[PDB]
Image (tube, coloured by chain):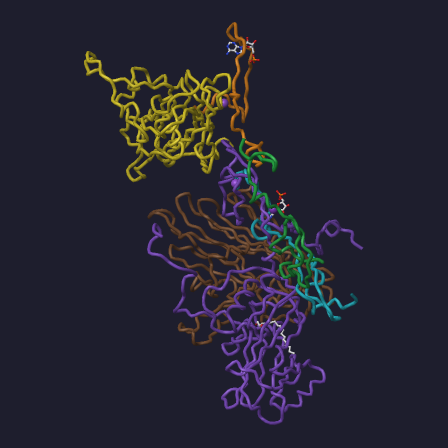
Chain colours: A yellow, B brown, C purple, D orange, E cyan, F green
Amino acid sequence: SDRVAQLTIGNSTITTQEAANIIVGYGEWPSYCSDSDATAVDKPTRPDVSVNRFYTLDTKLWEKSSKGWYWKFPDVLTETGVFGQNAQFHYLYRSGFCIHVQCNASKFHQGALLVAVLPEYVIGTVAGGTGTEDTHPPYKQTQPGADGFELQHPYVLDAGIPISQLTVCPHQWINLRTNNCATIIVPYINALPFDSALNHCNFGLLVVPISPLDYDQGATPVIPITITLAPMCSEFAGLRQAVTQ
Amino acid sequence: SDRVAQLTIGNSTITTQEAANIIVGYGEWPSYCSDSDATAVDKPTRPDVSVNRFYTLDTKLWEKSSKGWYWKFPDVLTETGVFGQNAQFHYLYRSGFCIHVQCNASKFHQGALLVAVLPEYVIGTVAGGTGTEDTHPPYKQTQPGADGFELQHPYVLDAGIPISQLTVCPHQWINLRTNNCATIIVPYINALPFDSALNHCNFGLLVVPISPLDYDQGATPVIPITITLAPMCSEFAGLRQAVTQ
Amino acid sequence: GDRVADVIESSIGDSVSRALTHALPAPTGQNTQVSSHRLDTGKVPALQAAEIGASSNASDESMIETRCVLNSHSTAETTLDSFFSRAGLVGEIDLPLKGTTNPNGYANWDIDITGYAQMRRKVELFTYMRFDAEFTFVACTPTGEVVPQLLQYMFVPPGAPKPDSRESLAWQTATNPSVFVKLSDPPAQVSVPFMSPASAYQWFYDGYPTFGEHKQEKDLEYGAMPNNMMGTFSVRTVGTSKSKYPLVVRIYMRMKHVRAWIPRPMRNQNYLFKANPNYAGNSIKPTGASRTAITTL
Amino acid sequence: GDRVADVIESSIGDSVSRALTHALPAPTGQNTQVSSHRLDTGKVPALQAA
Amino acid sequence: SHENSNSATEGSTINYTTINYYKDSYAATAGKQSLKQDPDKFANPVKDIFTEMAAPLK
Amino acid sequence: SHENSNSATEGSTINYTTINYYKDSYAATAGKQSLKQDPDKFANPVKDIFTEMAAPLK
Ligand SMILES: Nc1ncnc2c1ncn2[C@@H]1O[C@H](COP(=O)(O)O)[C@@H](O)[C@H]1O
Ligand SMILES: Nc1ncnc2c1ncn2[C@@H]1O[C@H](COP(=O)(O)O)[C@@H](O)[C@H]1O
Ligand SMILES: CCCCCCCCCCCCC/C=C\[C@H](O)[C@H](N)CO
Ligand SMILES: [K+]
Ligand code: NA
Ligand code: NA
């Protein structure tokens, strides 16, 4: 009655029988932009059901040696479905998200993933190793698209900050003996009312194993982690031709 | 609180800790025959507790290759206890039944049995294979008694009808990962108020594996299926000497 | 008088059939209500437990975001009378001149409608059926020709003398009902009431009609329900001399005022014999079409 | 004007950010209340689900 | 009219609307049946009914 | 009478007056239609209507 759940939005429904409640980031639900916070004058388009629905984008395999991965929002969706089209045809975009990370095993497997949302997740580089070279991460590392990207140094989140404190951000854990999914609702976070879905990623989603995956020889060894997410309260403005970047 | 149950009738009690609710056939409970539906004029005998009780009649072994079995009612009981005696001494009989099929395994076994009740289950023969010979099933196949009988062609219920549609009849499933029994209550079904317990079987009970039994070498391989049933609201009339057929 | 408590408090004799369900009027298909997103724990419409024996209770509204739809689609054509009150062929009777079968100018047909698959498959969807019927008799020569010939049809209930010739005394028909009609006239048509000694006809009877040992030789009687045996339909050319023409009488039955109980799986193997569910064991076919793989259309 | 039901009943456009928490005044550290032994079934404060 | 109650449906919980010209009611037309239905009898014949929102087995 | 509303015209803004002897209304005669007309729908479907006396383009 807290372990069981159904998430229905658009023409999509998700079920889980081993949930751990739901986190609503910073304690607030997604909402549309008010007439006082807004600044752009054109009437926005709010496609509703055609874009606020669940999209299943990627599956990673959790191995005994995995380091962890991250995805950037709204980047993961800019090329998918009606949402993508809207993000490409409009200069301005804004929306919240319902993120549902899935991972099931058996009562004989073990391990724990930390699933967190970090706003303005700026990636850093190792500065040539010695720290004398002012290098920058390439586009494919900053905006990895649906495939996501693997962390090189999880302990410092590839940005010189401690993953040990990442729990100060909206998060849940997928501890195999307890649950098989994490659900996080995120409101629109930014210092502007609307922004470009292409040039700016509002937050990053991190899925990192903190207690390594383990099991005895003979138990199913392929343990996938699937990422499903749904935009919420999507709004677009500043219409022109489609642009991919 | 729906998974747990106790059935007490007569001097007999059944318990289960892995139930799946109870089915009441065609939505109605067994009842005695009304003075307006009745036609025979003699005062009936309603033995009550001595005959409306649970009788455990048979145990079959579920094997990875089992085809399924059937029993005929009231035939399965005509030679057992005080019920049998009454059925033999009287021309007329009528009653409902509470059927409880039992089958437990382990959280590591798997398989699913379809347990259904089919009124007027007339058995057909394969017509000499070619379909040119008008053969008929022998008494031992139409009224198999307590031992029941194994289906030759489960797909067509040995009667030229699809088992895929048998769920249009009162039924439950025993899906090992979920429950260990099926309970079905059946009212008296017939186009007459009373009938012969010997010449006419009102319905048949079918127990058929649809998802085959399976388990790894080393797990208990003997998985019995036991049949327990109780007449309900039994009434008899037209008394004379005992007759077995 | 009753004095011991268990007798006073007993339910022995309760004649009222306690019913868990009841009928509601449903002249049209159900409507669709507006629905929105639900992001909840505890509520889980999509998850079911088929083991219970009931069908899923999940509806469109709870699985996707729906609009409002006012459904005025009628449910009238799926009533029992709509489905069954359509005349279909249930019997053919031949009256040839030079023949092996009926060269004597009369014929007796035991009333059994299970000789034709279309009609049979439909009524066998139910176990018990109660109804009235309209019988129509279409007569002509084998080429479909109409000739100036007079016929007599007689209903012979069980126990009445079956005619044994075109000149049988039984054709006096002082009590049985007979119809006299010409082939040149439109098809004869009559109404028949529900005649069984039982409350309903039953297409399936799992039992024997009599007591005794049920030895191999009296196994052809398994499944025989006298309550369904309404008698014989006899027809003759009305004359003392042989008719000049060969005839065929086709019998159509249209049920009306129908009630049915206990639905069952529908026949999926060819029928072979009247009132008997035998099927060809060597030619057991799937219920429907098949394909090469489960991952391909 | 709006006439089809899904439009009338929709929440498209709600500008009010529904908030699950609110601020309370807290000028000092919280106090401690007297407590005693508890020997109970059902009540289990110590057990959590991180 | 003033006929006999011969119809196979006399005493039915649904009323029909028919035409007839004979003294026997079974001679009447099929007419129009009443549109009531009870799916539950076959589709949901459980003793303790469960909701749509609940988990069927608890 | 007491028949079914089967007619192809059930729900028409013009009422008909027909004869029938069957339970299905589509079996009825054609009857008499109602004499309404709306020429403007085809002959004058302009947004801003102009008078007979005026110069159509001003
Ligand atoms: N099984 C059904 N089939 C068709 N229409 C139905 C059915 N059940 C209910 N309705 C219709 O829906 C209305 C009842 O809705 P409710 O009160 O939620 O059961 C009635 O006015 C019926 O016309
Ligand atoms: N997080 C907190 N930090 C410091 N003081 C608090 C906090 N929460 C509540 N209090 C104090 O405790 C009182 C409320 O106790 P209570 O009604 O049980 O929440 C107030 O008068 C506050 O001064
Ligand atoms: C003047 C001629 C009138 C013709 C009379 C026709 C009477 C027919 C009564 C309808 C009987 C319904 C069918 C009953 C049983 C089945 O055909 C089979 N016996 C099933 O075994
Ligand atoms: K409706
Ligand atoms: Na449910
Ligand atoms: Na706690």
- Residue C65 in sight from this viewpoint: yes
Please give the name of the residue rendered at 68% of the width and 69% of the height, measured from the top-left corner.
Answer: B239
C167 with respect to A119 (left or right): right
Examine the rendered structure and indicate whether residue B173 appears above or below residue B244. Answer: above
Q: Determine which quarter of the picture holds residue E50.
A: top right
Q: Residue at x 56, y 82 (%)?
A: C146
Q: Nearer the viewer, residue B59 or A169?
A: A169
- Which quadrant: the N terminus of chain D? top right
Q: Look at 64% across and 71% down and name the residue there.
A: C134
Against B233, residue C159 (above or below) is below
Q: On the picture, is C297 further left or further right than C137? A: left
Residue at far right of view: C1
Q: Residue C105: x percent and y percent? A: 57, 89
Q: What is the count of numbered marks? A: 0
Q: Residue furthest bottom?
A: C241
Query: Residue B227's spot in the image, x, y percent?
Result: 51, 55
Residue A23 % position (x, y): 46, 25
Instruction: Say which quadrant the C terminus of chain D sits in.
Output: top left
Residue E25 position by quadrant: bottom right
Q: Can residue B10 be seen in the rendering of this structure?
A: no
Residue A114 coordinates in the image, percent (x, y): 37, 25
